Structure formats: C-alpha cells, structure tokens
Length: 391
Ligand SMILES: CC[C@H]1OC(=O)[C@H](C)[C@@H](O[C@H]2C[C@@](C)(OC)[C@@H](O)[C@H](C)O2)[C@H](C)[C@@H](O[C@@H]2O[C@H](C)C[C@H](N(C)C)[C@H]2O)[C@](C)(O)C[C@@H](C)C(=O)[C@H](C)[C@@H](O)[C@H]1C
Ligand code: HEM
Image 1 (cartoon, rainbow, N blue to C red):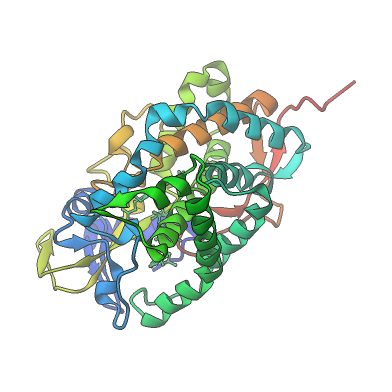
Image 2: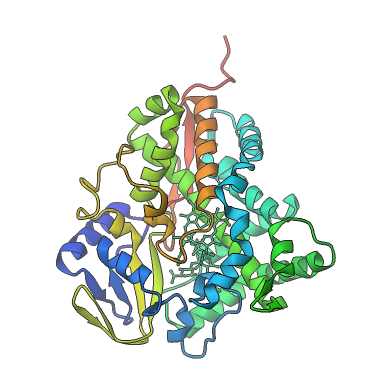
C-alpha cells in the first residue's frame, strides 16, 4: 500500500483496486473496501460492521465512553449527552469568536509564513478548548499529544501492542482531562465537560473513566482534522488558482469550495470496522471477527459516484449529509457544522487580508503526514497582496 505522503501514487493504486479488486484482504488479514456504494453499505450496517476494534484485538477490552467505538443501542444515549452542543443554531453563535481569533492570528503573520503554525493549528485548538472549558496555556500540550498519536509506530492495526502503545501515548492527556472532569463536577460552567459529567445515561452518571475517555475523544476529534482541512483547502486552491478570484468576487461560493475540498482531499481517508458475523461485500466473502478498512478517499474518487471524479469542481451538487468525508450513518461527524463554519470563516479572512496565498513548494518545511491523515504537517505560504505593503 502506498503511504499517505505520496498522494499521486496512492490515488493511482486506489483507482486500480476499484477496477480490479474492490474488496481486498491484506497480509494482516485486514479487509479493504474501495468503491463508494460498498463503503456506504458497510458504514450503514452497524449490526454486521461494529465500530469496536477491540473485538479482534486479543487481550483488549472495550474502552468505556469511547463514542466512536460504541455501537447501537448504547451509542444513541451517549451521543445524546452532547448533540445539542453541536446544532447549526448553537454553532452559528460561535461565528463572531471564530472570526476574531482568525483575524488576530493572521494580522501578525507577515507575507511569508507557515499556514499551519500561524492559523490552521491555533484556530481549531482554541475553539475546541473553549467548547470544553479549557485554558489557552494548554494548547501546546494538545498539539504535542495529537502529533505523537498521529506519528505512533504502526503497521498491523490489530496488534495488541499497538493498542497498548496508543493507550500510553494518550495517558497524559486522559489523565489531564480526568482532572478537569473532577474539577467540573465541583464547579460546573456551561462548557461541554460540565454537560458530560452532570449527564445521566441509562439511569446513572458517567463514571470517571467513561467521562475522561469521552472528553479525550471530543478534544482530539475537534482539532486534528479541522487543521488538516484548512491546509488542504489552501493547497488545493493553489493548484486551481482561478478559484481565488471567484471567491473574492463572490464569497458566497466558499461553502461549496469547502465541500469540494472535503471530497477531493478528505482529512481522514480511511476508517475501520469489525465484522460481528460472516458477511459479503460486492459478492466477496468476509469472515466473522475480522477488521475492515473503508477507504473514504477511494469512495470520493469513484466515477460511479462522482462524474469526472479527479476534477476539482466546487459546482458539484454534493454536500450536507451526503459528505462522505464526515462519515455516513449513525457515527456521522457530530462536529460537521462547526468544521464547516471554522473553514468558511478561515478562507473568508485569508481572502479578505491577502486576496490569495501561494504555496512555497521549495520551502523545506512542506512535508506531508506519512500515515493516518491526508495532508501536510506544515504549509509554507507566500502572500498575494497584504495590508503591510507601502510606498
Ligand atoms: C471522536 C471521533 C474521532 O475519534 C478520535 O479522535 C479517536 C479518539 C481516535 O481513537 C484513537 C484512541 C483510542 C484509544 O480510542 C478509544 C483507540 O482505540 C483508537 C484506535 O485510536 C481516532 C480513531 C484516531 O484514529 C486512529 O488512530 C490510531 C493511532 C490508528 C487508527 N487506524 C489507522 C488503525 C486510527 O483510525 C485519530 C488519530 O484521532 C484519528 C483522527 C485524526 C481523525 O481523523 C478522525 C476523524 C477522528 O477525529 C474521529 C474518528
Ligand atoms: C474538517 C474536519 C473534520 C472531519 C473531516 C471530521 C470527520 C469525522 C468522521 C469521518 C467521523 C466518523 C468516524 C467513524 O465513522 O468512525 C467523525 C466523527 C466525530 N466527530 Fe468529526 N470531523 C471533523 C471535525 C470535527 C469537529 C470540529 C468536532 C468537534 C468536537 C468533531 C467531533 C466528532 C465527534 C464527537 C465524532 C464521533 C461521532 C460518533 O461516533 O457518533 N469533528 N468525524
């Protein structure tokens, strides 16, 4: 399998798999699914395709409060704890603050800067920290913890030792959040941690383990992908720069750009399930108790789903609930309205200040993530025209 960092090679490979081997078993006994229709089938059928990886990891037991790894009927009660925090009306109230953070961060940039260090990292981490009621002094901790997680040594995703390694890398974060949970129990505010520690799920409060693990999932979910998307947006516009001008003339076009970048370059290009029973996808027999890898990236480029799938085209009618890059079915991204707002406001503010940004391809800081996510660790950019220029 080509690594994430060589996008062209990876896309080439996925394309031949869609044609020649749409359901593929790898050397670890992991089963890969490449076509859009088949990815939807898998994601919709939660009884057959569990979100709990521990089923196939010997020695590992389910992680209490890990919403992303919990199946119906328990899933719905846990999601109901936080879903009201994430409604479009409630999220829309965050626009002024998102814009204030973005504008201030960009105002001090200069005309040559790393988009990630300046804005794509600090914006989403501030917004999710503020959602969870955590302090600014803790942002650097979160970036260190997400970075280590993203670069964890990893090959066979069913290895018991990988599960232990993840646990160890996230131990400091979960411990920190456990302390913050105990703190909010005593002195609640109206942040997300307060809501989760005071909630009653199926007749009782979440225990300390559950609440910390749920907090951990919310924190990680809330920044890594948003950071990656913003980078992917600027990098994709740089490859199709006629769109900078069009968005400057009509900023109403920015949400369509955001949707099309999501399709074209999903931050999270693959997700795993486990089979609860013997099943078949596209007539290919898959046994019980194995791990399944759904390639969102391959689904998004499938010509049966999207005409001329390798063309970047904001005029595509796709988006909303049909945005596969936010998942599909019961686990569909709780943060979607928020991700969409942060990225809309970021691009508006970039265009307002600079008109356009050019990616500096000769700057050595430009490096792709090698695994797990689809994007760049840093994106050195050059300003088109900035308020700093003078006679
Ligand atoms: C809450 C929803 C979000 O969920 C999370 O953020 C979870 C808390 C992470 O779970 C962690 C921690 C733990 C203890 O869970 C209880 C563990 O049992 C699982 C397996 O790993 C998440 C799944 C991570 O992904 C996984 O990493 C692993 C290191 C490798 C996995 N694969 C490639 C094999 C990969 O699939 C990661 C990095 O955070 C993905 C991020 C960046 C992402 O793009 C998606 C969109 C993410 O935001 C949502 C999915
Ligand atoms: C552009 C950025 C984002 C992308 C691409 C993205 C993507 C995804 C995807 C693909 C899933 C489903 C994973 C699966 O089915 O296993 C998911 C779930 C989730 N996301 Fe997002 N996300 C983004 C931003 C956010 C933000 C800002 C938040 C706010 C905290 C958030 C919170 C969550 C939560 C809590 C879940 C779990 C939902 C559940 O399991 O019921 N995400 N996300």
